[PDB]
Amino acid sequence: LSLRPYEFWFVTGSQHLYGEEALKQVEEHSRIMVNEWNRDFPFPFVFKSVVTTPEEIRRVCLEANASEQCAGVVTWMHTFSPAKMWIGGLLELRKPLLHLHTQFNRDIPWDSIDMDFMNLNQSAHGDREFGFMVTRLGMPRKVIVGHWQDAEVARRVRGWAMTAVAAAVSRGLKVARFGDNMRQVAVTEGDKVEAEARFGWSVNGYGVGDLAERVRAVSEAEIDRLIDEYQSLYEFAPGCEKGGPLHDGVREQARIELGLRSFLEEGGFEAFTTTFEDLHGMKQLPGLAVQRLMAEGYGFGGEGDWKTAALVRLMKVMADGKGTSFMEDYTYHFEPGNEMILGAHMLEVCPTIAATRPRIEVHPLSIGGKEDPARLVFDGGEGAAVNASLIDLGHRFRLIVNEVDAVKPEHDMPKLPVARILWKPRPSLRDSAEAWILAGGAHHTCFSFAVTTEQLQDFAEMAGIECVVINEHTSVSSFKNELKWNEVFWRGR
Amino acid sequence: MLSLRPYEFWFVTGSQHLYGEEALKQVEEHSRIMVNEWNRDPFPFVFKSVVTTPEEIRRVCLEANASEQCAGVVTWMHTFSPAKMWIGGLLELRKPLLHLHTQFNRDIPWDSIDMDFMNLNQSAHGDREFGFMVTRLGMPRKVIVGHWQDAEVARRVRGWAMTAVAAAVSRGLKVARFGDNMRQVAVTEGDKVEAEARFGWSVNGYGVGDLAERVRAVSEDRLIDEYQSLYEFAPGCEKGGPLHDGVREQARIELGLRSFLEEGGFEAFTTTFEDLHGMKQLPGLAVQRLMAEGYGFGGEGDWKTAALVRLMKVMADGKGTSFMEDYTYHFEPGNEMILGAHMLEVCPTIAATRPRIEVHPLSIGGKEDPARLVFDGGEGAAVNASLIDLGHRFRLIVNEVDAVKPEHDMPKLPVARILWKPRPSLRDSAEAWILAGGAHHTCFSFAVTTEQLQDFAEMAGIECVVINEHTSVSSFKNELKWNEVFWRGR
Amino acid sequence: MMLSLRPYEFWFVTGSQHLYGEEALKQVEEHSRIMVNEWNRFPFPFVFKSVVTTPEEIRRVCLEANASEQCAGVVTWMHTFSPAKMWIGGLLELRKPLLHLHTQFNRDIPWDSIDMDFMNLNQSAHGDREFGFMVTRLGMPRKVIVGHWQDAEVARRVRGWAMTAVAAAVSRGLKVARFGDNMRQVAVTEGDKVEAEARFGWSVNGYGVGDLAERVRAVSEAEIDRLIDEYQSLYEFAPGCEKGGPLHDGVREQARIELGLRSFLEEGGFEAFTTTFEDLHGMKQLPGLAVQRLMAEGYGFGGEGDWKTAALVRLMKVMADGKGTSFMEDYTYHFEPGNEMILGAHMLEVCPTIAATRPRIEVHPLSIGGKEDPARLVFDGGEGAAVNASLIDLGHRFRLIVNEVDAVKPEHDMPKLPVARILWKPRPSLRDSAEAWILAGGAHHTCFSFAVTTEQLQDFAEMAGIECVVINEHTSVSSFKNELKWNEVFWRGR
Ligand SMILES: OC[C@@H](O)[C@@H](O)[C@@H](O)CO
Ligand SMILES: OC[C@@H](O)[C@@H](O)[C@@H](O)CO
Ligand SMILES: OC[C@@H](O)[C@@H](O)[C@@H](O)CO
Ligand SMILES: [Mn+2]
Ligand SMILES: [Mn+2]
Ligand SMILES: [Mn+2]
Ligand SMILES: [Mn+2]
């Protein structure tokens, strides 16, 4: 779906107390690091000034704050960089911060190491004084410690940069709701205002007839063109091929796909929701059309679930677009020793989780009482994964993350007419769900194979919301205590 | 004339067996005398027995909780009524509690008063001990002190009785939203879930296609017969070749709205002008008429004001109460006043003029020239109430205003309008209103008092701020700071 | 002279939407430009920025406000309805003092004219309210001024607030130089410099008095002569203190300190400094006339290492346009029934901008510092309304305390009092203010101003996010105690 050319500003801190020539060794050391990271992290590191004064620090932050291509700031105290200088800038920095607690040389030059070296590569105490200052200001930030060349440091920096880029998409992110929330449903509700203060989301509701007229203007020739792209991608079920009568169903989806994309592109929407209780002017419920916009980059939520729509977009950004989709727990496999969750949804499951080459099928749909819709049908993949809900507790949001394991279906489901994925939640179906329910997790989630818990925890930190994680170490007792103690901490905020 | 259930108020009298069973006979006799006399002229009072045991106390409360006719409980400690007895019942009670701290005789019978009297007529301390237990439980309740025949006691119960009835309406209240919120608008947004938990409001959004289908149905028309039975018309009248399908389209909108609202049980609704697919006209004259039946309305998807209007119309007994919006100011020194209106939907029950039907263009929403009631609003003391979501909790903001007759007419203004002089001044009240965060949409009423709205906040468990003749802006900011610290969490 | 001020400007931003055409934007734009131009005829220039209509326009002007070191405050006005969720991103970014001007181009309703087009364009009655909601919902502090934009009171209030916001923009830059540490064992002059740099923006750092001693040794004796010619330009000399007199030595020393002090503080960019009599190595006198001179030029100062008051004196002087503001200390009480007064001085350092007598250079012994007889300006303070302000550290947060007072002309001369002085009558009473002051924890060091109001100090405290308590004619000690209690619960979190 294409991102801004986001970049990370690498701001090195120092002080005049060793001279202007030591300020040159620092500028050199910093440029060598930035340039050597950029030999590759699909976002360039931009080396900015060595900063030595309150004013230089304050302005790199002011500038960071304002450049929309800056998606995070990485700050490293090369020398001692007295941290009160950093206050004024740190107060203004509202882009994500990473404190790279590193060091140019990797190993203590025994036989060399004198005071001249001790005056230059003193990161070991410089970063701690800067660390104090960021803590003393209550500022959320990521802290990674190691040599700037170590392979794990880059892993952590790479993971964090993906998160910071999501954070930047989040700032802009405009969501288009096509109809209200499903009536009397609770979890898909919330304060769009608060989500806009907290996450930057503009969560935009347009009457479904705005969408209905967009899909009528769509030429039959544009439909013909997309259909050849389906042929290029997705095997068709019987009767869906251009001859069979199911094609007016497949072509309508493709028509909806074109009315939608036209609309979402005209407004700069990167996420959107539909509602089956409001489909006036529509022939079908958006299904394969929704499935495809997801795979391209859009976030979706069913039944007006703007929260998960935004969440889906955001987790697509973190995953580099891969292995991520809106999700809904639909039934359980409770077979002792083999207990599984079956995740699916009405129509809308993104093909980027597919281990089967997706296949356009067409089936009836009781819900909404509109045309028998077309939709991609496939089995979700296998491997470690995460399932994420963002909910509104009223006074604040909570992000719930279940580390799960998706499994290859042992048997077929030929009568199941929508996309399907199986997964065994950690630490068990029993405790994951109890924990999930105590946490209040929604039924809508964003399932992903590529977003790691650490990234979502890092996103929550950046946004300043609670993130609770259900994984293999989760005990329900202590998890109850986490929810009690986190609640104490997050009031006000 | 939107009807309420026959709401009743359960008088409960508390006592104990320390004085005997003929003392109880007198406690029951006094209470029936009181309830009976109050019932010779709002809503009936029902004497509900003298309760004397935890279990009798718990019973009547459970009974109150489940009686959807019970809009409030009125409790009175005729004697000492040991208050722990009351815990398990007060814990259950979820209906408005009025603690009527009263006494049967008015005077101390000096010549006669003996220990058998002070055993029996000891509300003086029994009510204080009940006082402690309700306070000790944190419970919201009204307290009214005075003789049960005292005229002022009556005015205050009648007032509280109106708030309690509105509170019961609140617990039923179902709101239909035709379209979402107007776009990028902040104050009309909020948390429908929380508002359901705090006020009992069921706020549910129907796509306007649903309301568009129900007005593709008829009764031709009978409606227009009574339009002329009520309202002046303008050129655009009946023949009115130009503009009559304007009025026949609002009349159409009115009957499909009413059919949708009466079908689903909605006493409040909202329209948004940004979703009008299938509507030839943004609703206007239709909405003003539904409001005058008692419906709550909020423009641009404003459910909180929609609900608020409903409850204030119920508090007001249908009178002088309308969706409102500060539209423009008149800063003329010494004569500063606000022009409240809305793009169409002002309820005629605030009119001091005969309502006139006009049909004028309306750019907004890009639909046909809507028909609407145009009229000048009345004068006299009033309140202007906004209810906002601060994110963690709701805030009811109430401004006492003085509505004024307009000295100059506004002959090319196509909407109904009212002028008021807000207390204590345009400059300070607006400042307070803005510090408090009050919406542009409000409920104006001539017949809801501030005390009522405050009492509703108590029932509801929310902050109520009031801007009136005694408001300083600087102390008002303190009140906001101090309230916010009390109300967060709660 | 007077300490220099960056050219500060206030940005006038006006909000509206696209639901009305391109043409209405044109009229809103002209309306604001008219209002701004008529305003510049206010203390500092107003700059009409833009009509903002989108999220990204609101955010950019806000980013530009934070960045613009010339911008002292943003003045927002919602001409029409400006859906406030648009303003979230901008308001969350804005860190400049915000005034919300709730106003209206036209003063009166055109009764014969008014129609939907007018109701669609002059919508502030609600557009500002929708904006008031969003600002309140983010918990941001702002000023809110309501009136027609030509209103005289609207101007008086905007001038007060602008003076404040320029004091705030100085506070962010503000650099304080402590020559010496706190007077040993003193509590109220202590505090958290880190917290104060985070809250108010003040950079507060210690130099050894050695750094200043050596800077005064490098003063020419030719510039010292140039300065005495300026003392003759300005100040009456007590017997034995002009050129040739026995105690004119002492004035020269205070000339030398002044010129060294000024060179240290001009070199570093410091607008406020502190000295301590317990640390005077390398100086022949505790600085005094020098300080008095420097405060007169607009420097903040606090005795005994008191950076908090030093910063406060500089800020209030900015608020007061340099006029009638001075460091102050309650020295002694006149308790006479019906004439209760406080004599307020310091041991040397009272700024002459509060003088009612023409200041007189004098030289007297001073036990305190252990150094030579210090020269100093001596005068009787003027009379009238004034505020006495103190900023203290409660440990977890700052508290601004402001007493309204009425300065009085001395009825009886004080011939054997070697220091400048002022006499004031604290509202509502001496016994009640001192009680409320002591309960508030007021320092003995104050900043005293004839030209700073309480509403300005409150506005300053609102901008910084700190508690301000005012002691004046309406203050009763029982309700004051409750204010302190209830304020504490509010200010604990934040
Ligand atoms: O500028 C800092 C300095 O060089 C050393 O960090 C200190 O002396 C010891 O921390
Ligand atoms: O005569 C009843 C009487 O009310 C009680 O026994 C006590 O005074 C309450 O302490
Ligand atoms: O909410 C303000 C008012 O109701 C309307 O939004 C304006 O007239 C048109 O935006
Ligand atoms: Mn669903
Ligand atoms: Mn409106
Ligand atoms: Mn909320
Ligand atoms: Mn002192």
Image (cartoon, coloured by chain):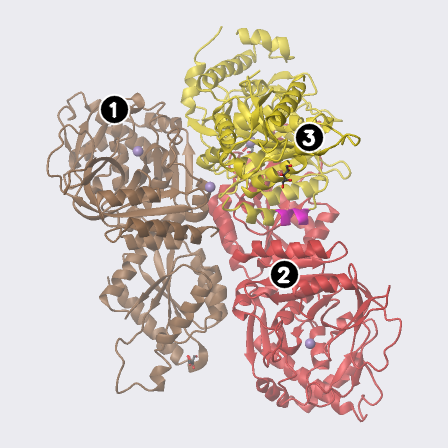
Chain colours: A brown, B yellow, C red
Q: Which residues are magenta?
A: B473-479
Q: Nearer the viewer, mark 3 or mark 1?
A: 3
Asked whether residue B197 is in view, the answer is: yes
Q: Secondary structure at mark 2?
A: helix
Q: In the displayed structure, does residue C234 sit left or right of residue B479?
A: right
CA gap between label 3 and label 1 equals 68 Å
Residue A152 x/y as whole percent: 24, 64
Name the image quarter holding residue B345: top right
On the image, numbered disc 3 is attached to which residue? B103
Q: Is mark 3 within 8 Å of ligand 2?
A: no
Q: Chain of mark 1?
A: A
On the image, numbered disc 2 is attached to which residue? C166
Q: Nearer the viewer, mark 3 or mark 2?
A: 3
On the image, numbered disc 1 is attached to which residue? A365
Q: Is mark 2 within 8 Å of ligand 7?
A: no
Name the residue rendered at 54%, 35% in the picture.
B460
Residue C278 x/y as whole percent: 63, 84
